[PDB]
Image: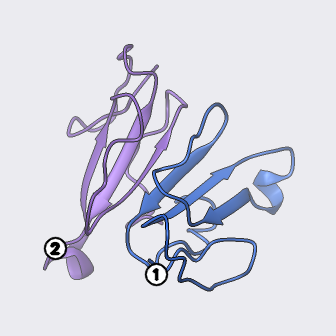
Chain colours: A purple, B blue
């Protein structure tokens, strides 16, 4: 599987973990300047727990920087 | 917790499951006409498994129709 993963711009090939999990959360400066975002290759949709939002996909390729906020 | 959930437009209050999980996948008509989408209140980021993409949040309120595609 080809995990984009952070912080490292764009990339891939793990192989171990079989997925790409993406997640984001807010803080004082979100709104007027963008969200705090983390992109990675693990295995299982990682934990969320409390003021956060995330998504995951199988698809090697899919772990990029999402619609300016998630959307 | 207040799960929007599908198909039922917008709504909430489950309470059992403590979350809102959102997911989407494509088929022949995605591209030129939109993705196939499902929005719900369970408990745990539900399974994905194969040509699919999803996300989840704690946040009562959050389970709406995402950036025209996810983004």
* Relative horizontal placement of residue B58, taking residue B38 as reference (left or right): left
Secondary structure category for the residue under label 2: loop
* Relative horizontal placement of residue B67, taking residue A10 as reference (left or right): right
Residue A48 is situated, as x and y percent measured from the top left of the image, at 31, 54
Q: How many marks?
A: 2
In the orientation shown, which residue stands out farthest toward the right? B28
Tell me: residue B51, above or below residue B19. Answer: above
Residue B67 is situated, as x and y percent measured from the top left of the image, at 56, 68
Residue B22 is situated, as x and y percent measured from the top left of the image, at 56, 60
Query: In the picture, residue B1 is in which quadrant?
Result: bottom left
The chain letter under disc 2 is A
Same chain assignment for discs 1 and 2:
no
Tell me: residue A48, above or below residue B4. Answer: above
Report the residue at 86% width, 52% height from top. Answer: B29
Residue bearing the label numbered 2: A27
Residue situated in front as seen by the camera: A3 or B23: B23
Report the residue at 48% width, 64% height from top. Answer: B17
Residues at marks 1 and 2, CA–CA distance in whole angstroms: 18 Å
Report the residue at 74% width, 46% height from top. Answer: B26
Residue situated in front as seen by the camera: B15 or B35: B15
* Mark 2 Cα-neighbour bin, 10 Å: few <14, some 14–19, many ≥20: few
Secondary structure category for the residue under label 1: loop
In the orientation shown, which residue stands out farthest toward the top? A15
The chain letter under disc 1 is B
Tell me: residue A8, above or below residue A14. Answer: below
Residue B40 is situated, as x and y percent measured from the top left of the image, at 61, 65
Residue bearing the label numbered 1: B61
Report the residue at 25% width, 38% height from top. Answer: A6
* Relative horizontal placement of residue B65, taking residue A32 as reference (left or right): right
């Amino acid at each position: 599987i080809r995990c984009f993963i952070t912080p490292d711009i764009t990339s891939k090939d793990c192989p171990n973990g079989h997925v790409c999990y993406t997640k984001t959360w807010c803080d004082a400066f979100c709104s007027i300047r963008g969200k705090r975002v983390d992109l990675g290759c693990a295995a299982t949709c990682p934990t969320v727990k409390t003021g956060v939002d995330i998504q995951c996909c199988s698809t090697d390729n899919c772990n990029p920087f999402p619609t300016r906020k998630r959307p």
